[PDB]
RNA sequence: UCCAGUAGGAACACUAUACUACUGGAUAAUCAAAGACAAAUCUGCCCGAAGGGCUUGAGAACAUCGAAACACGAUGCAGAGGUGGCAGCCUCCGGUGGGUUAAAACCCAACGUUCUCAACAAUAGUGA
C-alpha cells in the first residue's frame, strides 16, 4: 500500500571482491520489524541468507554465507544493508530484502518484498557475441518443415535480444535462455521452423542486439 | 542440526479447475511456524499462508494450508489461470531459516513427441578455433526428456549443456536445445556425431546424426 | 464492599457454610452473555507401605502477548476423563484447516503448559 522496499547496490564484481546492498524502507518504522535478505540463483530456488531482529538487533546468517556477510540497519535512514565480503561466483544471484509481518497480522510470514537487485560475481570482461548460423540441412528437417537458427556464443554480460527479419517473423521462433559456459562467457541460440519449400525463395536473417557492448550483428542463416 | 523442508513434487501439471496439492515435510518439529509463497518468473515472491494454516490477507480463499504433525500442505480448491507459478514452503521456527526446493505448477496438455533436428558446427565457427554441435528437441510435452551425445559411438559426458523454453503461450509445449562443445582438434578427428532423444512421446529413442563434411 | 447469573468449594461421593473465578451490575443491583469431569474405566512396561488435587504461592522450561523467534518486559487466562510413573490408545472440550452445507448438525486432520517445592485440601451433616 504505502509499505514499500527498494534495494540497490547490486552490480558486477570480481571474486573475492566486495559489495554492499542496501534496502530503503518506506511506509513503516524499520526498527519494529525483522528484516531478512533472501537470494535466488539463476534457475534455482529461494535461499534464506540473513536477518536482523527488532529491539535486540540480534543477527542471524546462513551456513553458506556466515562469516563473509554482515546485515545491519540504520534507524536514521530507515534502511537495511548487507555487507558482502569475499564474494565468489557461487554467490551470483538476485537479492531481495523482505520484512517479517506483524505477529498478530501475519505471524512470521514475510509479507513485503523488494523488487530485488542483481549481483553478478564474475571476473570476465564485457564482450560482444559471436553469431554463427545454424544452417537448415537435410538433418534439421521433418515433413514439410525445416528448422534453422543462429548460435549466439561467448558474450557477457546479459542480456541479448534476438529477432528474425527485423521482427516480421515471430511464428515458431524459440529463443533459449542464456547458459553460463565454463569459459565464463554466456551462450544461447534462437531457432525457428518454416516450410521446406520457402527455403529457396525466402530470406532469413537473425538480428542480434547486445547493449552492454553496443554490439549489433545480423547473420543471414542459409542452407550450406 | 539445521531443520530441513522437503517440498514435493518438484514439478506438477494441472488443468484449470483441478484441485492441486503441494506437500512439504519438516526434518523435525517446526510447530506451526510455516509459510507458503507464490512466485512468478523474475518477480518477487508473494505470501499466501502464514502460521501453517492462516490465509494471508488479500489472498483468494481457494488457497489454503494445513498441518498434520510435521507435514505441511498447501491446497488450491480450484486452479485458476493466474495460479500457474512456482510455490515455496518456508519454516521460521528456528535459525537458520530454510525454504523447500519449490514446486512449479504447469499447464497440463496431451503428450507430444519432440521433433529432433541436428546442426553441425558452422565453417565460420571452425575457422575460429572451437566447435559447437547443436541438437534441438522442438515442441514437445511433457517436459521430462533425455538427450545423450555420442561421437563415433562414444558416450559424451560433461562436455555439453542444454536449455529449455517456457511452456509456449500457444500450444503449451516445451522446446529444448542441447549443445556439445569440442576443440577443433577433437572435432576434426571423429567422423559421426549423434544425439539420442528419449521422450515419453517416442515409443523408442530417436537418433539424429551427421558425418563431418 | 455488596447483589445476580454461572462454574468451582480442592484425600470417596453428595449437600450446606466458609472461600475462589468469570460475566453483568449497585441495594429497585436489570436484561444478559457465558457454562468442557458426558460416556467410558482401555493397552504395555516400571515403581510404592498405601496410588484418585477444576485449590493456591514461589523457582526452570516452554508458550502467549507487548510493533518483539533471541535479548528485555508482562501473562500463564483451556484443556478433561480413563487413579503413581513413563509410553500408547479411546472419548470429551477448544479454537484452527479441509469436506458437506441453511449450519462446526455431521465427517476428516493435526494441534492445546509441563516440571520442581511448600502450603492448604476446611467446619459440619449424609453416605461408598
Ligand atoms: Cl508463525
Ligand atoms: Mg580431448
Ligand atoms: Mg457472588
Ligand atoms: Mg460443587
Ligand atoms: Mg466485577
Ligand atoms: Mg462421568
Ligand atoms: Mg506394589
Ligand atoms: Mg480427578
Ligand atoms: Mg519464550
Ligand atoms: Mg512502543
Ligand atoms: Mg489424559
Ligand atoms: Mg492421575
Ligand atoms: Mg496405569
Ligand atoms: Mg498418560
Ligand atoms: Mg473436534
Ligand atoms: Mg468449515
Ligand atoms: Mg491431546
Ligand atoms: Mg495454553
Image (spheres, rainbow, N blue to C red):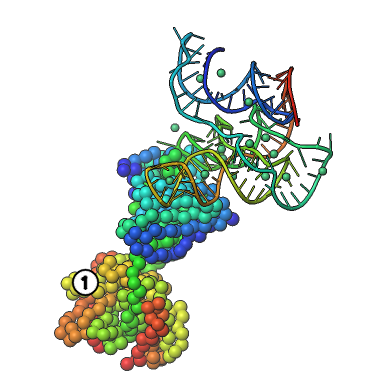
Residue with the mark numbered 1: A170
Task: Locate the C terminus of chain A by quadrant.
Answer: bottom left
* Quadrant of ligand 18 in image: top right
Q: Position of residue B107 (x, y in %)?
A: 34, 65
Q: Position of residue C4 (x, y in %)?
A: 52, 18
Q: Callout 1: 10 Å neighbours few (<14), some, many (20+)?
A: few
Residue drawn at (26%, 68%) of the image: B170
Q: Quadrant of residue C63?
A: top right
Q: Quadrant of residue A134?
A: bottom left
Give whichever of C28, B75 is nearer the camera: C28
Residue drawn at (37%, 60%) of the image: B18
Q: Position of residue A27 (x, y in %)?
A: 34, 41
Look at the picture and state if B109 lies above or below A95: below
Look at the picture and state if A136 lies above or below B102: below
| Chain letter belonging to callout 1 | A
Give whichever of A190, C50 is nearer the camera: C50
Would you say A179 lies left or right of C65 here? left
Amino acid at each position: 500500500s504505502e509499505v514499500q522496499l527498494v534495494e540497490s547496490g547490486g552490480g558486477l564484481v570480481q571474486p573475492g571482491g566486495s559489495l554492499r546492498l542496501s534496502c530503503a524502507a518506506s511506509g513503516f518504522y524499520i526498527s519494529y520489524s525483522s528484516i531478512h535478505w533472501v537470494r535466488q540463483a539463476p534457475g534455482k530456488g529461494l535461499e534464506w541468507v540473513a536477518s536482523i531482529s527488532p529491539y535486540s538487533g540480534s543477527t542471524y546468517y546462513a551456513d553458506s554465507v556466515k562469516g563473509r556477510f554482515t546485515i545491519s540497519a540504520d534507524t536514521s535512514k530507515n534502511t537495511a544493508y548487507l555487507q558482502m565480503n569475499s564474494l565468489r561466483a557461487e554467490d551470483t544471484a538476485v537479492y531481495y530484502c523482505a520484512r517479517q509481518g506483524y505477529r498478530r497480522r501475519s505471524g512470521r510470514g514475510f509479507d513485503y518484498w523488494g523488487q530485488g537487485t542483481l549481483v553478478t560475481v564474475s571476473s570476465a570482461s564485457t564482450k560482444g557475441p559471436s553469431v554463427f548460423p545454424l544452417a537448415p540441412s537435410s538433418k534439421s528437417t521433418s515433413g514439410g518443415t525445416a528448422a534453422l537458427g543462429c548460435l549466439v556464443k561467448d558474450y557477457f554480460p546479459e542480456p541479448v535480444t534476438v529477432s528474425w527479419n527485423s521482427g516480421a517473423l515471430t511464428s515458431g521462433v524459440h529463443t533459449f535462455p542464456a547458459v553460463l559456459q565454463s569459459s565464463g562467457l554466456y551462450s544461447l541460440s534462437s531457432v525457428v521452423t518454416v516450410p521446406s519449400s520457402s527455403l529457396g525463395t525466402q530470406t532469413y536473417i537473425c538480428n542480434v542486439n547486445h547493449k552492454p557492448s553496443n554490439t549489433k550483428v545480423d547473420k543471414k542463416v542459409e542452407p550450406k | 542440526s539445521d531443520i530441513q523442508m522437503t517440498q514435493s513434487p518438484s514439478s506438477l501439471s494441472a488443468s484449470v479447475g483441478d484441485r492441486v496439492t503441494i506437500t512439504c515435510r519438516a526434518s523435525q518439529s517446526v510447530s506451526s511456524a510455516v509459510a507458503w509463497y507464490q512466485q512468478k518468473p523474475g518477480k518477487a515472491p508473494k505470501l499466501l499462508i502464514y502460521s501453517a494454516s492462516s490465509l494471508y490477507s488479500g489472498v483468494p480463499s481457494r488457497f489454503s494450508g494445513s498441518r498434520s504433525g510435521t507435514d505441511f500442505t498447501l491446497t488450491i480448491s480450484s486452479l485458476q489461470p493466474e495460479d500457474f507459478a512456482t510455490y515455496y514452503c518456508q519454516q521460521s521456527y528456528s535459525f537458520p531459516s530454510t525454504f523447500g526446493q519449490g514446486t512449479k505448477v504447469e499447464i497440463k496438455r496431451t503428450v507430444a513427441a519432440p521433433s529432433v533436428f541436428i546442426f553441425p558446427p558452422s565453417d565460420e565457427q571452425l575457422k575460429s578455433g572451437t566447435a559447437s554441435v547443436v541438437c534441438l528437441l522442438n515442441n514437445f510435452y511433457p517436459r521430462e526428456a533425455k538427450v545423450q551425445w555420442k561421437v563415433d559411438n562414444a558416450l559424451q559426458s560433461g562436455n555439453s549443456q542444454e536449455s529449455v523454453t517456457e511452456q509456449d503461450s500457444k500450444d503449451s509445449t516445451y522446446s529444448l536445445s542441447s549443445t556439445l562443445t569440442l576443440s577443433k582438434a577433437d572435432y576434426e578427428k571423429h567422423k559421426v556425431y549423434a544425439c539420442e532423444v528419449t521422450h515419453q512421446g517416442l515409443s523408442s529413442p530417436v537418433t539424429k546424426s551427421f558425418n563431418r563434411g
